[PDB]
């Protein structure tokens, strides 16, 4: 059990976001991205955190409806 991905920087990234978003569309990507980034670009983590209200003090403060600059 150990999936290996050679790349993950462009499409994949987007996928992740969408993944979470799909679950938490209310929130803005900008915030969904930040989280991911902080969560080793992990969808489960982000949600897990949110669900576990374990959202960092830097994210929980971030603009819940943060947008993504350019794309």
Image (cartoon, rainbow, N blue to C red):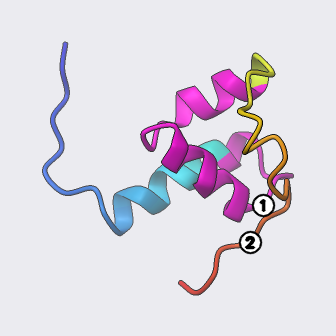
Please give the label number shown on residue 28: 1
The x, y position of residue 45, in whole percent, is 56, 27
Where residue 1 sits, quadrant-wise, is top left
The percent coordinates of residue 18 (x first, y second) are 59, 54
Query: Which label belongs to residue 67?
Result: 2
Cα separation, mark 2 vs mark 1, equals 6 Å
Residue at 68% of width from left, 47% of height from top? 22
Image: magenta residue range: 21-50
Q: Position of residue 36 (x, y in %)?
A: 54, 45
Residue at position x 68%, y 50% in the image: 21
Question: Observer-nearest residue: 25 or 33?
Answer: 33
In the rendered picture of this protein, how many numbered marks are placed on residues?
2
* Image position of 61 with respect to 1: above or below: below
The outermost residue toward the top is 1
Residue appearing at x 74%, y 21% in the figure: 54
Please tell me which residue lies in front, 30 or 25: 30
Q: Residues within 10 Å of mark 2 (few under 14, many from 20)?
A: some
* Circles 2, 1 touching at the beta carbon (< 8 Å): yes
């Amino acid at each position: 059990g150990s999936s290996g991905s050679s790349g993950m920087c462009g499409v994949e990234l987007d996928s992740l976001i969408s993944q979470v978003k799909d679950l938490l569309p209310d929130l803005g990507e900008g915030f969904i991205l930040a989280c991911l980034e902080y969560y080793h670009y992990d969808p489960e983590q982000v949600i897990n955190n949110i669900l576990e209200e374990r959202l960092a003090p830097t994210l929980s403060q971030l603009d819940r409806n943060l947008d993504r600059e350019m794309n």
